[PDB]
Each structure stands twice: as structure tokens, then as C-alpha cells.
Image (cartoon, rainbow over all chains, first blue to last red; front, side):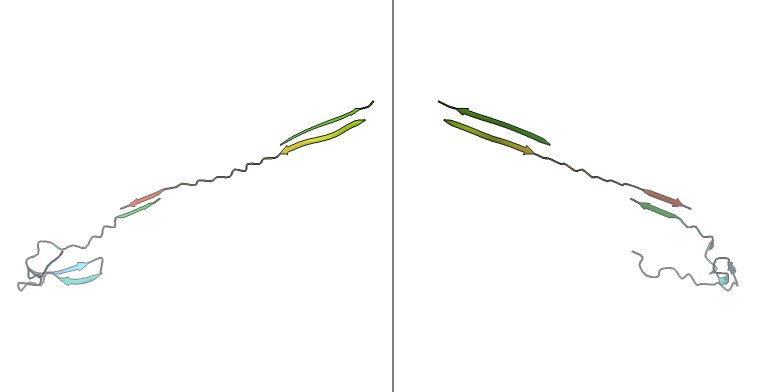
Length: 50
Length: 46
């Protein structure tokens, strides 16, 4: 199970670290700490009918 | 199928006579029908 909030992932550190998500097509502000946050999609489909 | 019919007649006189028939018939029919369709699909996409 995922448990409760441990890291402050919205600590911006005074930076204006915009990222454009091509997926959501919107500008988002990353926290100062996060090493990367990226939006490339992967879609991984198993059908198995018998 | 089978038919198996036999017949005998007899008479004797100086008077006694017999005329007699016995026959039995058999029929059989077996009918068979069967079907079995099996299949599988996989689709893995990335």
C-alpha cells in the first residue's frame, strides 16, 4: 500500500522551473528538488482470449 | 436390419395337419453427431 505524505514535493525553492507537458499540453511548475519529471507515455497491452 | 421368417406345413392321413409360421424382426439405428471448436488469441502491443 501507498502510505502518507513523506516528502514535500511542492517545495519550489524560489525557482520558476516551468515544464511543458506535451501529453497534457500544459505548463507545470516542478519543485526545485525533483531530479526529473517527464511525460513520455508508454502503453502496454496484453490480450489473451481462450 | 434383419427379417428371419420360417414356415412349415404338415399333414398326415389314414387325419392331422399343421400349418405354422414364426418369424422375428430386428431394427437398429445409431446416429452420431459431434462438434468441437477451440481457439486462442493473444495480442501484445507496446
